[PDB]
Amino acid sequence: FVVIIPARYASTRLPGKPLVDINGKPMIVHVLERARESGAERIIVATDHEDVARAVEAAGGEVCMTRSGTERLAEVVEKCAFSDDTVIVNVQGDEPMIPATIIRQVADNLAQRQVGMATLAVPIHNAEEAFNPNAVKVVLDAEGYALYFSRATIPWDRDRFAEGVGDNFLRHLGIYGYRAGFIRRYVNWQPSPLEHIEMLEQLRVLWYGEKIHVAVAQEVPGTGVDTPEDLERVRAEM
Amino acid sequence: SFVVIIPARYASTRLPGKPLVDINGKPMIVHVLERARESGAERIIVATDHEDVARAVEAAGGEVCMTRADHQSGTERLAEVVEKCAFSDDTVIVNVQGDEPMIPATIIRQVADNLAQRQVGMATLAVPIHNAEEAFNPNAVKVVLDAEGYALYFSRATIPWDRDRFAEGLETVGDNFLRHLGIYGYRAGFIRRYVNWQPSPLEHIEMLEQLRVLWYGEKIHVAVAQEVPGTGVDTPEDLERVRA
């Protein structure tokens, strides 16, 4: 398998996000450390910023210069001319501590199943987080395919509440695996009315009647780096 | 083409002897039987474990199938009727609830035709939600569909979540919420087997039996009700209202 890291540069709160220093190396290079450890055969950082490109290349990383998240992966997939059956894992460029094991988990999951997309989830063990619409919840069928993803608290467990949340709740992790040919197709699809309601791009897949596999992360990752607080945390932990 | 089975629930708190509650010279169950005849069903069976219900249905010329006194879900009670009436597996069955004396005949036929066309486990119906109160009412089951009208998920939670709208307040709602209506269509062969599948854990979490279908990888088709039907009689108020 192959790892593509779409470094998003613009951001309120964290200006030069991929290039922010974490103990002597830039954040994007740290995500490069992890991807390599996953055993990936290609690790491509996708960006349209020269300064980022020179930082990855100085660390020995491959870069693909791009001209909407998934659409950036489509461009890299075309520019690299990967075959349709190539397994691709999308790792966000704000995750310098993502464990390599979970990168490999999603790849093996996609490899062993006949399905367009695989992804990962972790259990929710607290109510604040269960009713937080920033925590995307997911409900599964017996084989681990996603029935639905939502910012609503699903499944609605009227028994856990009301006691002052049990063990039925999963939080969706923003790491994805797909075959290259699926990515090619996916981005040509008209968007769905659902995705703009929920603000979850992944519902396009379920809307079109396609399947997404979800495994429980074999290792719970730390939160990404979106804020100065997240940056101070990650700085002290690495 | 199709058969209607009405599992009349007898014991209710706050109705009580529900199917037999008089509505202008006829008991509720007989009214539901009238609606079912109008749909062109080739058979309309009321399933019951009570003799008083049996006789009231039979006096109006309605077919009855006695079912076990051991407690049964509505579905489990249909599956007994299927066993007892010896319908072939490909027979199309519509489950119509017994507290719906005003149910339009056209929507009964809509569900049968919907099942007959597709090659799906279940067909069912939905209606749009207008009030934020109802959107946020856990007694109102929501459903979100895929592009071909198949349920992605049913839930008492407010799905789909309108994040930009609900970041500002829970006060208001767009025009996209769907409320699930408890009428169902399926094949005799399917129901026979489905009542023996072990429950999904989802079932007891959401208190929604139909999630069993989705849990085991089968599909439920959902059309928007062709004629918005009136509320089921579940309270003395519903009963006073329906008598007019």
Image (spheres, coloured by chain):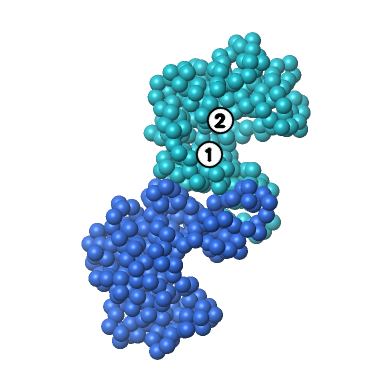
Chain colours: A cyan, B blue
**Mark 2 nearby-residue class (10 Å; few <14, some 14–19, many ≥20):** few
Residue A150 can be seen, yes or no: no
> In which image quadrant can residue B72 be found?
bottom left
- Name the residue furthest bottom: B25
Q: Earlier in the sequence, mark 2 or mark 1?
A: 2
- How many marks on residues? 2
Q: Mark 1 points at which residue?
A: A201
User: Chain ID for label 1?
Assistant: A
Q: Which mark is residue A3?
A: none
Same subunit: marks 2 and 1: yes
Decide: is A175 above or below A40.
below
Marks 2/1: CA–CA distance: 10 Å
Label 2 SS:
loop
Does residue B63 appear to the left or right of B95 in the view shown?
A: left
User: Chain ID for label 2?
Assistant: A
Circles 2 and 1, Cβ within 8 Å, touching? The answer is yes
Expressed as whole percent of the image width and height from the top left, the position of residue B138 reads: 57, 62
Q: Looking at numbered disc 1 in the image, what kind of residue is underneath it?
A: Glu
The residue at the point 57 percent across, 40 percent down is A172
The residue at the point 34 percent across, 68 percent down is B106
Q: Mark 2 points at which residue?
A: A69
Residue A223 can be seen, yes or no: yes
The residue at the point 41 percent across, 52 percent down is B149
The C terminus of chain A - image quarter = top right
Q: Looking at numbered disc 2 in the image, what kind of residue is underneath it?
A: Gly
Decide: is B73 above or below A22.
below
> In which image quadrant can residue A27 be found?
top right
Expressed as whole percent of the image width and height from the top left, the position of residue B89 reads: 25, 59
Expressed as whole percent of the image width and height from the top left, the position of residue B195 reads: 37, 60
